[PDB]
Image (cartoon, rainbow over all chains, first blue to last red):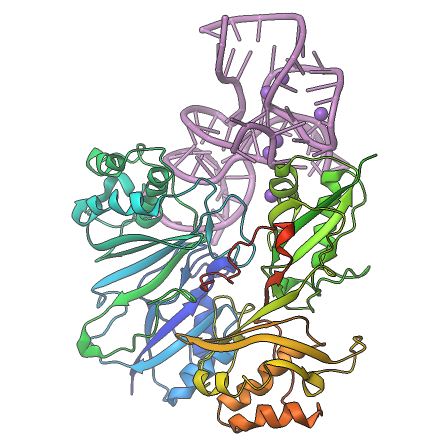
Amino acid sequence: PVYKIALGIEYDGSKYYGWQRQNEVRSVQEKLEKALSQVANEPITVFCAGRTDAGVHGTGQVVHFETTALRKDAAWTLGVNANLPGDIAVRWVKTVPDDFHARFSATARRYRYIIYNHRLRPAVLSKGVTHFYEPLDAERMHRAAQCLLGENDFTSFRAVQCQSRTPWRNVMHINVTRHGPYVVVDIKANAFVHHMVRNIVGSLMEVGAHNQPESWIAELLAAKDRTLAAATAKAEGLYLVAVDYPDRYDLPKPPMGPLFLAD
Amino acid sequence: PPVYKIALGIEYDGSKYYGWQRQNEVRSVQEKLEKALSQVANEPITVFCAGRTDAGVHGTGQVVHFETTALRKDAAWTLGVNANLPGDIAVRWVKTVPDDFHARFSATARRYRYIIYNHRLRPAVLSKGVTHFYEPLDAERMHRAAQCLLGENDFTSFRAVQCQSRTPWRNVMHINVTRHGPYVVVDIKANAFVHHMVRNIVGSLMEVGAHNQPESWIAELLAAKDRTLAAATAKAEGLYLVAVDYPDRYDLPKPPMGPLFLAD
RNA sequence: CCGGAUGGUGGAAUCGGUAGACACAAGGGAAAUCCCUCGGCGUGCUGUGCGGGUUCAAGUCCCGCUCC
Ligand SMILES: [K+]
Ligand SMILES: [K+]
Ligand SMILES: [K+]
Ligand SMILES: [K+]
Ligand SMILES: [K+]
Ligand SMILES: [K+]
């Protein structure tokens, strides 16, 4: 018998060279497979809903695999976790049909960017938040961002190493708010082009610091040029908070956080 | 030569340090902090913290002071020192204070926050900054079973052996337990605390929360004046020295105590 | 006149904080993905035209020299 299982993985990529399995470096996927394999007692290969670059964290990542071995729930949750490193962890298990597929079944991914806005660098979670010196204007930022909403040509916020096809994406919602000293950027789209978020954030920050007009983000978008927008934003601050899947699969959706961040 | 009494608001992540207490043998927050301060003042510097934390415990409201004959502009102590500090340690603010100031002795009351990730499966993000407690906690029940420690009591049951205070008596300003999504936070403020006082109150408070003991237990323990009766000391990675109290005359800056996104 | 002269190329570095972010190449190993290297030395040092200086700290300031 083949069993298609879906796991909700969570992690802290600060100590990993990303998710993708590199035969020469540390990858969340690798550590995750080693464990799953020990439980199923057979070589296991997983498929994630969205690979994160080296540095980016995850709290809503979703993966699936097929094992011939039958393990009770705890085996996949409490079990795998017992084999996983402290930074990586399983949030929930759920057997799914054959028509499910972490990546291809995903209707839209969602990210959150954590910006610690203070003159002096942070200490706690120094690898989990991006530190931005210049005073940000959450208000102004949010406004200068609604122009990216909908379907547009994110070429200006694209990448040259983008292995995807058409640079067109559909943004469900992009909001920027401030939590005390923090500034958070929540963005949801059907998908994103290489470094799309870290780029939108980069240019959004310049605006926030009043180094550019609100109209700049819009001018960039239509500029269809990358060498016009700000430089890619730091990684340590990006969190893959949540992925969208058809309600028919009935996958559990726990708080996306990160941490104390309201859902 | 002029002597300058300076007060720094230090913040850090003790996950990688054997505590604050400078030890000529291991990594201590205080040591790394002094090395830096010294490079700035270009003279051996010795600091005094408002409350030493044990190996593991973090800090976001810690306050220290020192005296240097060297005159450095503000940035030198803030942006400067930080530039010499490790990434986990950091200065939050500088402030020259009078001679009658003293981080420890001037402190009117310290304050802590305990972060409990209440979920069957262990956390990944901040795995060293939050305490993972398997059994389902009852924030409500916990808070209630705690108000009995409020005020001045004999915290012998929540004390320790390696304790140096000549008296295990303390005055609790307030102890509250709330739940943030999967988290359970315990905020406690007192004039001072006896060795492992907080981690102990939390330990026994958790047993109650998990319904392994009655709300009346915390109270029975307190009056029991016995330690071998209460729960075992709670984990360290979850304790944060969020804030210290000082006379308003000193006018020290009081930024958000957090940790992180935690409302002030 | 004043503002610049930093990597192979752009292009950064909080009204002195401890280089080269970021982007785009190149080269090598495991059409493209990916690791590491890509100032000079080598057997970590000195290096932000060039020596000298001040400062705990200099690309970041004071002085003499070359060119926009
Ligand atoms: K630094
Ligand atoms: K430098
Ligand atoms: K530098
Ligand atoms: K010098
Ligand atoms: K120079
Ligand atoms: K000069």
